[PDB]
Amino acid sequence: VHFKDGVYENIPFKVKGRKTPYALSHFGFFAIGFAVPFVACYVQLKKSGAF
Amino acid sequence: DEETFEEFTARYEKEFDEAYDLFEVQRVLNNCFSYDLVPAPAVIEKALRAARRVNDLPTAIRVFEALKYKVENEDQYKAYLDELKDVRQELGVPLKEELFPS
Amino acid sequence: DVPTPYACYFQDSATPNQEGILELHDNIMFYLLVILGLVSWMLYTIVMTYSKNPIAYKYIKHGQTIEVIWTIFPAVILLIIAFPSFILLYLCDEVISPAMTIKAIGYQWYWKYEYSDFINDSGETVEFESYVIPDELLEEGQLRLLDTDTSMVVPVDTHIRFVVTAADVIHDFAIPSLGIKVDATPGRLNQVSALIQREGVFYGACSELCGTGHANMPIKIEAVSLPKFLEWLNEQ
Amino acid sequence: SPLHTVGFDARFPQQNQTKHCWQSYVDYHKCVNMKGEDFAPCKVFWKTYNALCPLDWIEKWDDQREKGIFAGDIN
Amino acid sequence: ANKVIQLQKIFQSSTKPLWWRHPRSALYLYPFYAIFAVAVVTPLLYIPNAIRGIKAKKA
Amino acid sequence: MTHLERSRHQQHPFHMVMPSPWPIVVSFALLSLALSTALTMHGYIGNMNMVYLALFVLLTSSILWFRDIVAEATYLGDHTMAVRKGINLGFLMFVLSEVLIFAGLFWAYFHSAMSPDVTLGACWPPVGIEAVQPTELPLLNTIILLSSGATVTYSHHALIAGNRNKALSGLLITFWLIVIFVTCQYIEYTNAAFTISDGVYGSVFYAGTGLHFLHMVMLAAMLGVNYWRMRNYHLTAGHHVGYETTIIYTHVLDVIWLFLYVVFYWWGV
Amino acid sequence: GRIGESWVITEGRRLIPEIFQWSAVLSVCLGWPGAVYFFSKARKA
Amino acid sequence: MVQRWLYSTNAKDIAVLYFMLAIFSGMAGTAMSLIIRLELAAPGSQYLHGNSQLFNVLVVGHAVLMIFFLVMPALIGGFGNYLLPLMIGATDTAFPRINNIAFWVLPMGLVCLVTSTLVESGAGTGWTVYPPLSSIQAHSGPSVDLAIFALHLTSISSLLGAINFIVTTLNMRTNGMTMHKLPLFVWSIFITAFLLLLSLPVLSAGITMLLLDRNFNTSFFEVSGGGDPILYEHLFWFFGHPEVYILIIPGFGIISHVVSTYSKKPVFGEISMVYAMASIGLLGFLVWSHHMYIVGLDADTRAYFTSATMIIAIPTGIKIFSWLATIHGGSIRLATPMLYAIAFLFLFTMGGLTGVALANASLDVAFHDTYYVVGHFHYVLSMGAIFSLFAGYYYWSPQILGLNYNEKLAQIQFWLIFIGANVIFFPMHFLGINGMPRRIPDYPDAFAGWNYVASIGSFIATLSLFLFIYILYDQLVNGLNNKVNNKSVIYNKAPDFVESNTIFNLNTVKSSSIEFLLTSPPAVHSFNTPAVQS
Ligand code: HEA
Ligand code: HEA
Ligand SMILES: CCCCCCCCCCCCCCCC(=O)OC[C@H](COP(=O)(O)OCCN)OC(=O)CCCCCCCCCCCCCCC
Ligand SMILES: CCCCCCCCCCCCCCCC(=O)OC[C@H](COP(=O)(O)OCCN)OC(=O)CCCCCCCCCCCCCCC
Ligand SMILES: CCCCCCCCCCCCCCCC(=O)OC[C@H](COP(=O)(O)OCCN)OC(=O)CCCCCCCCCCCCCCC
Ligand SMILES: CCCCCCCCCCCCCCCC(=O)OC[C@H](COP(=O)(O)OCCN)OC(=O)CCCCCCCCCCCCCCC
Ligand SMILES: CCCCCCCCCCCCCCCC(=O)OC[C@H](COP(=O)(O)OCCN)OC(=O)CCCCCCCCCCCCCCC
Ligand SMILES: CCCCCCCCCCCCCCCC(=O)OC[C@H](COP(=O)(O)OCCN)OC(=O)CCCCCCCCCCCCCCC
Ligand code: CUA
Ligand SMILES: [Ca+2]
Ligand SMILES: [Cu+2]
Ligand SMILES: [Mg+2]
């Protein structure tokens, strides 16, 4: 299949010409990664009765 | 690679006479200063007469600048400037210290 | 015998096996310091001089003399320290003419000790369990996560055979100052030997992840004199 | 010194000592099955399997012999 | 019988995706997609009980 | 063919596969299988109906992937000499990996048998275990397998030579010989006096010979695929790659079973 | 013969300053935990 | 858009998905190591309320994410899938649909490992998962099953990708390129693909047999049925050691390219570098029981494994001296990739010399489950493989993306991780030699000193990772401006001494591999008429 060429064309995410700022996508994506260990801790400390 | 020093000069003397434009004179000069030796005075003279034939003055200035990097002492730099005295004078080539004096 | 704050070395030795382990560590570190001195120096004096070299030596691509020489040199060093490392391996594996045997069994977060030589005046098996003293029950001056409610008592200058196993999962009998470390596997019996040269208390810990209580299962050993051991043995 | 225990045996010279216990227990019970329970040098086996073998192991093998489930070949 | 050449010209002159060119391909692809949806959703609808420790009452 | 016409064709022989949905649909069936089996093994799901559905969807989704490789080679002409050579080399590296899976099962057997544990009786086999005798139904199986590596040899060489009937008969016989092997192991299983629950012996025995049982069911499915393709004129006298991969498969499984029969049946009994 | 000063003097002038700069770097990479213990309560009271 | 990224058969697009997933996973594994280092800061319960099972759960999650979900999908799934076809002239990979399934099993293996920590109590077993601690008596419920299925899905991924890497290298080279003419990075992915092919099937036997004991009443490792726990360790470690080399060799090939580019010299003794990489990959199958020195093996078994482990130091030291020989007499250019490569040569040597002490079985009695071991393998995995991963990104991303990065911001990032990594792991050797066990949430009070120092460095290094996340943002929003202002490096090679500024503009690139000769973002149809070499 024929695709396009250029600078922002070989990535799956949109960086330019978007309504919402790209900062919400960039740092929201890496925030969710950093936040999954804390969700696990919350569930397990809420099972031991610590909370 | 077993090449004696005498074979080194006789091969790069032949290589400076065949260079036909600026790209060739700069490419041959780059490879001549990339060994573990300082080229003989008779090789430096043929590199100056090759840059005259392509009409380029900065390449002839850079020849003596590389010479002062490659020697071991400053008295080895002087003895070259005392052998190539006429040629630097006959073609009108200045030294980089003489051109931008500090 | 006990760890100390900001310590950067072995705990003091009480057996000839731990004397020899330390001797081999120091012998090896003599040669690892020559090698680190070379590599760090060549790295430093290459960046400082060739980051300011305007003409690269692009025609140097191999050397027969140096490449053979630097293939042989690491083999000589490696062979020099393998000689005492083989001798220590066979000197610690031998258990010849011991005078007493003690069994140690690991459980889900306590130890257990059994004496079955029947030397005591009534000829039974002496056995007890050893538990860490809980934090709520500590008396002021006792050591957290180290002191136990009962300890193992052995005599000095006596060759001892230790027999180690387990009941539920894998544990590990380990005392740093005696040169002892051996897994405790459900199903088999391993053995180790010791000979203590001075009196005192020696502390250890479990060394095979065994679940939630892996940190609460310490080992404490007291070495006393021979008349003192017979009195303790004949009572407990 | 009044201390004595079993010594080095050339059949079992390695760190693994599992078979040393089990063979002394097996030899002892078959020594009393034909030469009688009481035998001066039949106590040699009894000392060795007691010295270096867990009390919970002996407890299990005794119960198995009662039901005829001991896997050792003693009869 | 032999139908290699006839299918060879149907396939090579078709605009549709590869898995759609055969005239019989509708009968496989329609029911597979429905079955594929049930087989993916249903295990996911059980993780809430697994976290909450509720077990099925097959008794 | 001038320069104008040569421009309408590729300059390299390699295959440019169009985008397909199958690789990401197989991955979802793999996760649905993993999530269902763990949940039913522990009671969170009442029965085995959801595990059945996940196995059915992993199966019919690989079929469609295989269906798209038939069309790219029979109706499109995309399998040139270089594409053919790469396919053969990928299959040899697949079987080398599967062979080392059995190599790990032979380690576990020898670890348990050379110095047997005392709770067994310090004897191999353990006391009370009645094992399978070699000169029996397992000896009929080793002959049935050796007999199919020579009827598959003359079918392959009858296709190169252009004989159709002889080719079609030497494959219909290899099919029913692997089928006979499969039901013969079924009889040998429902009659054995021990179970996979019977300690470490019933674990290493049924693992080594039970994995081999599963490959044979896969091997009989491959000879049925070749049968449809050879009878319906897909395979030609010089271009039959789906057939050579099957042939190499029947010969490695023959050697593996030979090893199982010498270790699990003659030496270990 | 040889023109200029001996190669020992020329090379000596270039390496002696670098020996001291090497030993002052490797001491920082390997001796920095010694400074933490210097300002501790456990040390020398 | 849907069918370009869910139906993909292009090797460059798939390699971008790999890197996206790899970097999202290093976030989680770094967050777990930060929670771990906060609970180890001081004696007593600190942040987890005395839940020791939870502390053990986070340690398994930390190791699995860093190894199987960050370093393997980035060094191999990312750089291997992107640069190997371009360096040999291939128009694609062999088997493009196999190449796509080997990515889409990793997202499904993450929604198996994450749901494993949320169900019942999680798996508090260690990343080696020894039985009987991991059997149904000592670990009930479905947590250890869901972790095994996660490991199964990463094995399908790495095996399928390895079969694809091997066929592509042997079958699809371009005109004139013979196996003696391959770039050194291509050799490093080729040899790694063979270690994966011969070690992964032994691990799949071990952990499937562990699943059978738990759920199907089987006695491979159960002691009441005759089984043996020590069998599992033989089967697990026969895959383990080959794995650590599956993690360093691709980084050996990256280091070769970077060091040669920023010296303007070819790699010294290039042919003996391939022979050394093959010798290390072969000797990594004969040394596995140095991980079982105290479980009761025979004394003659232990003397063999001592000498087998030591002799892997000879081929590795050839690669160390070879790298120092190419930078000697060079013209060094200290861009950001060159900084990591020089730190790799110094920090990998230190980690490898503490392994030589561990190689002797007599000395390993004082080095078992000791923090001293933890200090060894974080010097070769976190100042080793991780430093080579940074060196790669700064080396190839401007070409791959068409966007430049802020140079002086990147040198701040390098110094913050070099300082902070040393602070975490250097005192770990002091704790171990004095006798501190590993895998404990709590310790005696005499170990408080060095444990406080290491927890501080853990904050320094996490700040350096957050600066790297901003550098990615700046490159993606301001990458085109970084080329016209003076905030980034344009040329990784500068003009030669006698080469003038305008002659240099005739040939800007002087490269011994194809990849720097393409368009900046390489075309989706990169070769039509095949490339040709002499
Ligand atoms: C890939 C391997 C890897 C990496 C990188 C790390 C990184 C770190 N590890 Fe760990 N660790 C292991 C592998 C690794 N570790 C293993 C196998 C174990 C043993 C498990 C066991 O005991 O069961 C272990 C155990 C372990 C323990 C033992 C806990 C205990 O025994 O219970 C501790 C304790 O502090 C620790 C700390 C750290 C720290 C502080 C870092 C941090 O310093 C990290 C520093 C640097 C970074 C912040 C990472 C870079 C960030 C990226 C996302 C890279 C992105 C790059 C690009 C894409 C270009 N690790
Ligand atoms: C990148 C990963 C990686 C690499 C490359 C290595 C490399 C080496 N490792 Fe390591 N190792 C691990 C990852 C790694 N390791 C992990 C994760 C563990 C713990 C697993 C766990 O328990 O969870 C571990 C644990 C481990 C053990 C088990 C110890 C124990 O658990 O008790 C041993 C045993 O010998 C070992 C030794 C070695 C040796 C000799 C090398 C050698 O290859 C090093 C050779 C390199 C050099 C020697 C440097 C340069 C050489 C020269 C300059 C030559 C001149 C030198 C001389 C003459 C001496 N390490
Ligand atoms: C949440 C915003 C929704 C806004 C609502 C829409 C209203 C209109 C606004 C217009 C925005 C449209 C939103 C579409 C989604 C979107 O463009 O960004 C949203 C995307 C998500 O989507 P995804 O496709 O990447 O898939 C992923 C979904 N799980 O974030 C991101 O990945 C940020 C990722 C950036 C980090 C990657 C950095 C790697 C750089 C490449 C380097 C590669 C090196 C390779 C070397 C081998
Ligand atoms: C990369 C891994 C390197 C391995 C290093 C592991 C450790 C090996 C043993 C080192 C012994 C340290 C001497 C103890 C001094 C002391 O006595 O310490 C004294 C105090 C506290 O002592 P104190 O008050 O408790 O009691 C005793 C009071 N006198 O501490 C310190 O000053 C810390 C200073 C750190 C020491 C620098 C270490 C340099 C060694 C470099 C090794 C190079 C590696 C070689 C190649 C691998
Ligand atoms: C990822 C790579 C895979 C690595 C695999 C390593 C280990 C595999 C060895 C086990 C393979 C299955 C053994 C055959 C079944 C058997 O055991 O035979 C059947 C046995 C014998 O019947 P019986 O006990 O009633 O006695 C007969 C007395 N009348 O019954 C059982 O077991 C019942 C339990 C069912 C066992 C199914 C286990 C499935 C899990 C593994 C799935 C296969 C692995 C993947 C293969 C593609
Ligand atoms: C429970 C779910 C389990 C699902 C597993 C089902 C497995 C059953 C086996 C069915 C195989 C059908 C293949 C026919 C495709 C075909 O058409 O191959 C023929 C093609 C066409 O070439 P031609 O020569 O015919 O040219 C015609 C004249 N021009 O060549 C090839 O592609 C060769 C490659 C075939 C390799 C198939 C894959 C084998 C390994 C798969 C293993 C998967 C399970 C592994 C588990 C451990
Ligand atoms: C290669 C990389 C090298 C990087 C250099 C390291 C510097 C980065 C920052 C390091 C963090 C410091 C941890 C302090 C933890 C703490 O709280 O210290 C506590 C100690 C007191 O102890 P306390 O018991 O009272 O604690 C009570 C707990 N509540 O106070 C200090 O000692 C102050 C710190 C001393 C400063 C030294 C820093 C190292 C610089 C080295 C300079 C070169 C030295 C050369 C010697 C030959
Ligand atoms: C849990 C139970 C275990 C399940 C096993 C995992 C199942 C995942 C795969 C499901 C099967 C779908 C078919 C995909 C395979 C395929 O189609 O191979 C066919 C590919 C197609 O090539 P192409 O389309 O890429 O190129 C386009 C050219 N026409 O021919 C090849 O590559 C040649 C080499 C064959 C090697 C196949 C290997 C078999 C894959 C399974 C490997 C599993 C290893 C782990 C063992 C436990
Ligand atoms: Cu017992 Cu850890
Ligand atoms: Ca704490
Ligand atoms: Cu190892
Ligand atoms: Mg251990």
Image (cartoon, rainbow, N blue to C red):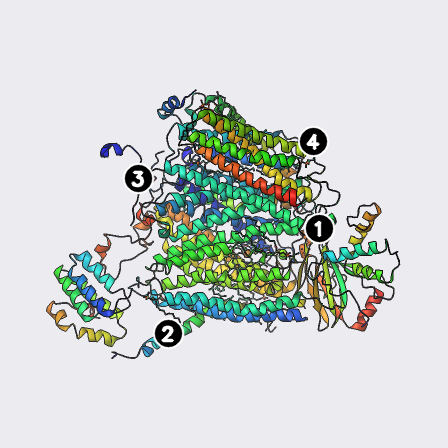
Closer to viewer: mark 1 or mark 3 = 1
Chain for numbered disc 4: E
On residue C135, the disc is none
Q: Is residue H330 visible?
A: yes
Q: Nearer the viewer, residue F189 or H66?
A: F189
Discs 2, 3 touching: Cβ within 8 Å: no
Q: Are marks 1 and 3 on the same chain?
A: no
On residue F117, the disc is 1
Discs 2, 4 touching: Cβ within 8 Å: no
Quarter holding residue H262: bottom left
At label 2, counting other C-alpha atoms closer than 10 Å, the crowd grade (few under 14, some 14-19, many 20 or more) is: few
**Quarter of the image containing the N terminus of chain H?**
top left
Q: CA distance from mark 2 to mark 4?
A: 82 Å
Mark 1 element type? loop
Q: CA distance from mark 4 to mark 1?
A: 42 Å
Q: CA distance from mark 3 to mark 4?
A: 63 Å
Query: Residue shown at 68%/32% (left/top)?
Result: F190
Residue at numbered disc 4: E57
Discs 4, 1 touching: Cβ within 8 Å: no
Task: Give amino acid for label 1.
Answer: Asp
